[PDB]
Structures are given as structure tokens and as C-alpha cells.
């Protein structure tokens, strides 16, 4: 399977992110770039709904089919949608090259038809000592998003 | 099971289309509106790929896993608005005819039902809704 997402938002933030899974239960490669970002770390998650009728707001919460706590490290408790942080350079460009073992593009709990979101602030990966850390990672507002679609 | 699609293009054509399927073995209800169209019939199809990196062009061909994406035509009234109210039992929101993650496209011309529908005016990726 291959998938793709066009990220867009109100601001200068935009990008394209590609997904590829060679085998049914194989790792998913996630790669592309996002620009218009402030230099530094930006939270990066799959959200539950592929509903962009009210912008990124209508995407709902982090995609969490197992009803677990927010995280990031793929070897510890997380939402399925938790993809940690992207890092923007001095020119505001975040080149993305990730391999994730928890998301999938087929079978149970796949992310096709859901929304990819890039955030205002860094994701604390559920490591903070506050309630918000366990829910959102304190990544703040949604800067750009798009629906994840099947690609050729 | 519910889905939604925001149709956009590089012209005036735009709309929102909703999909609801209460039963996995039953019909999908398709409803919404599209504005900015020329009066008359317009091709209305699910295309294979939910790839909008090149606008509607990257959506690929008419969706056909066997066409399954054959939703026929919408009718734009004289004010350029098409009211969409469709029940289709060929498309699905689950299983093998699943259209989630694919692209809904509205066309310049009428689908002659056998498809000569012309340019892709607006499109969007079909996403899971609450
Ligand atoms: Cu998020
Ligand atoms: Cu078509
Ligand atoms: Zn999370």
C-alpha cells in the first residue's frame, strides 16, 4: 500500500507526506517535507476523522482506537496516531523521513481516510507531569492538515 | 459508518458531500451540494486514488476494483447549484468496494453513462466522519 497527504492551512504552512507499507503487517515509511514552520520541533499526529469541513478542527482527537494514553516512542504506550515531532530548519523547512511500526495502511486500525496534522509547538511525547501531556502532548494548535488518501 | 468529502478545484466549483451507511450490506446515502457549476448535467465519480498532489489529475481513473465509482450525474440548476441526494448500493464505506481514502470528482460535462465527462472541475479525498 501507498498513501499520500496534502497538508494545507490558513498560514504559510503546507507540505506533502507520503506513506508506504510493503507488507500487510510491515513497517510504514513516512516521508516528505513541510514548510512555513517556525524553526524547531512540531507535533505530528494522525487524527481520528478525515473531516476537514471546519478546517483542522473537525479532524477530532489523536487517532486512538485502543483507548490508550498519548505517547510517541513506538516501544511504549501511545495513541496509534502518535508520530512524535518533525523538526523545521532555520528556513522553516521540515524534511520528514520516519519509519513507524504502530500505524498501518491496511487491515485493522489503518489510517487511510483519516487526517494528518502538523502542530504549533513541540510534542512532549506524554513525558510531562500534567493531564494535557497524556492527551495531546501539549503540541498546541493545528497549523496544517490533510486527509490521508490511497496513492498509486 | 459516515464519510465526508470537501470538493475544491482551481475554479469556482466547490461543495461538501456526505456519505452514510447504516448497514455494511446496505446502500450508501450520498448527499450535499455543489456550487459554481454550469446549468445541467455533470459527471460525478469516485476515482481510484485519494492523491490530490496534482489537484484532480492525480486521482487517477474511474474507480474499478472489479465501474464501482460510477455514480452517474448530478444536475446543476439554473443558479449553478446542484442538490445531491443519492442512494447507491454498489459503493461502500467498508469492505472491497470501500471508497474511503479515494477521490470524489465532479466533471465539466455530462457522463453519457457509457465516460466523455470532460475536465475535472473539483475534487476531494473521501474521509471518515463522526
Ligand atoms: Cu494532533
Ligand atoms: Cu470521472
Ligand atoms: Zn496522541
Image (cartoon, coloured by chain):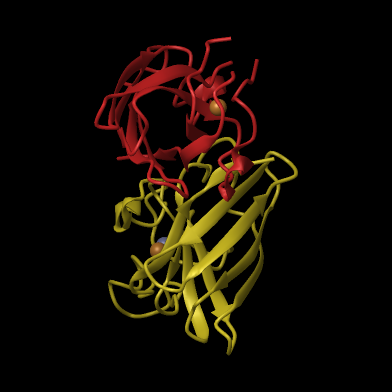
Chain colours: A yellow, B red
Q: Nearer the viewer, residue A127 or B99?
A: B99
The residue depicted at 55 percent of the width and 68 percent of the height is: A73
Note whether B31 is above or below A38 in the view shown.
above
- x%, y% of residue A114? 45, 47
- Image: A34 above or below A40: above
Q: Quadrant of ligand 3?
A: bottom left
How many numbered discs, if any?
A: 0
Where's the N terminus of chain A, which quadrant?
top right
Vertical placement of residue B79 versus A85, above or below: above
Residue A126 position by quadrant: bottom left
| Residue B35: quarter of image | top left
Locate residue A68, reporting x and y percent. 39, 55
Q: Among all residues in the image, which is located at the extreme bottom?
A: A90
Left or right of A136? Residue A146 is right
- Image height of B122 relative to B54, above or below: above
Q: Residue at x 47, y 71 (%)?
A: A13
Identify the residue at the far right of this view: A22
Where residue B31 sits, quadrant-wise, is top left
Expressed as whole percent of the image width and height from the top left, the position of residue A48 reads: 39, 49
User: In front here: B12 or B72?
Assistant: B12
| Identity of the residue drawn at 60% across and 31% down | B48
Give how far across and how far down residue A11 sits, in percent: 40, 72
Q: Is residue B91 visible?
A: yes
Amino acid at each position: 500500500t501507498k498513501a499520500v497527504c496534502v497538508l494545507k492551512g490558513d498560514g504559510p504552512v503546507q507540505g506533502i507526506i507520503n506513506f508506504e507499507q510493503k507488507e500487510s503487517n510491515g513497517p510504514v515509511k513516512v516521508w516528505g517535507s513541510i514548510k512555513g514552520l517556525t524553526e524547531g520541533l512540531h507535533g505530528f499526529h494522525v487524527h481520528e476523522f478525515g473531516d476537514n469541513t471546519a478546517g483542522c478542527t473537525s479532524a477530532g482527537p489523536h487517532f486512538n482506537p485502543l483507548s490508550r494514553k498519548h505517547g510517541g516512542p513506538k516501544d511504549e504506550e501511545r495513541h496509534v496516531g502518535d508520530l512524535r515531532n518533525v523538526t523545521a530548519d532555520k528556513d522553516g523547512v521540515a524534511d520528514v523521513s520516519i519509519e513507524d511500526s504502530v500505524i498501518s495502511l491496511s487491515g485493522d486500525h489503518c489510517i487511510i481516510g483519516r487526517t494528518l496534522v502538523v502542530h504549533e509547538k513541540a510534542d512532549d511525547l506524554g513525558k510531562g507531569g500534567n493531564e494535557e501531556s497524556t492527551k495531546t502532548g501539549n503540541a498546541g494548535s493545528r497549523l496544517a492538515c490533510g486527509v490521508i488518501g490511497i496513492a498509486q
